[PDB]
Image: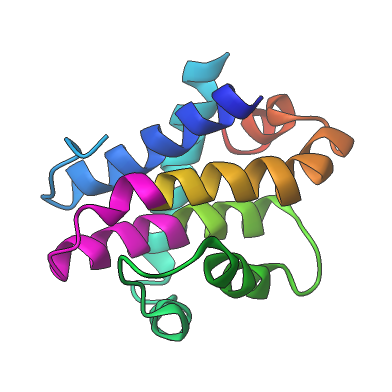
Amino acid sequence: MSQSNRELVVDFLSYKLSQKGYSWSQFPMAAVKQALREAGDEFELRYRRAFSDLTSQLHITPGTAYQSFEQVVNELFRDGVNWGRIVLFFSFGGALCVESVDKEMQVLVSRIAAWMATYLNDHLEPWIQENGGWDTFVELYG
């Protein structure tokens, strides 16, 4: 749901910020969150800086509009959606939040969280629901 997904995004972002020494104060569900957290770490374990070019293409500032974020994220889905690419999506948002804080734009993290929820509900849920819903995600990554 719009609320379920919003909560999922905030949890993942908060988890990543915490894990990396940053503040998260700027902000079965438990089974999905845990699975996503682990999926994100697993991926980052293999690719330490896989979104350098992507975040660079966006060069986010308080003046960045959603449409720009959307256009860049669309890059991850050039061949459509799959679970791994959804994990990349979450990981990408986490990296954007980290970068925002490093640039003293911590005000943007809640905004990125909002953009992610919107993008999730709009472009990824259609595929997620068609392929088993989050229960399938848990079944594959849990």
99 inside magenta stretch: yes
Position above or below: 67 against 32: below
Position above or below: 104 against 130: below
- Which of the two residues, 18 or 1, is positioned nearer the viewer here? 1
The residue range painted magenta reads: 92-111
Looking at this rendering, what residue extends furthest in the right direction? 130
Q: Which residue appears at 35% of the width and 76% of the height? A: 49
Number of marks present in the image shown: 0
User: Is residue 54 rendered to the left or right of residue 83?
Assistant: left
Position above or below: 36 against 53: above
Looking at this rendering, what residue extends furthest in the front direction? 63
- Which of the two residues, 22 or 136, is positioned nearer the viewer here? 22
Q: In what quadrant of the picture does the N terminus appear?
A: top right
Position above or below: 9 against 53: above
User: Is residue 100 rendered to the left or right of residue 138?
Assistant: left
Q: Position of residue 38 (x, y in %)?
A: 43, 41
Q: Position of residue 116 (x, y in %)?
A: 52, 49
Q: Position of residue 86 (x, y in %)?
A: 62, 52
Q: Which residue appears at 35% of the width and 64% of the height? A: 96
Q: In what quadrant of the picture does the C terminus appear?
A: top right
Q: Which residue appears at 74% of the width and 51% of the height? A: 123
Picture quadrant where residue 131 is located? top right
Q: How are the residues colored?
A: rainbow
Q: Which residue appears at 19% of the width and 55% of the height? A: 106
Picture quadrant where residue 5 is located? top right
Q: Position of residue 61 (x, y in %)?
A: 31, 71
2 inside magenta stretch: no
- Secondary structure mostly seen in magenta is helix
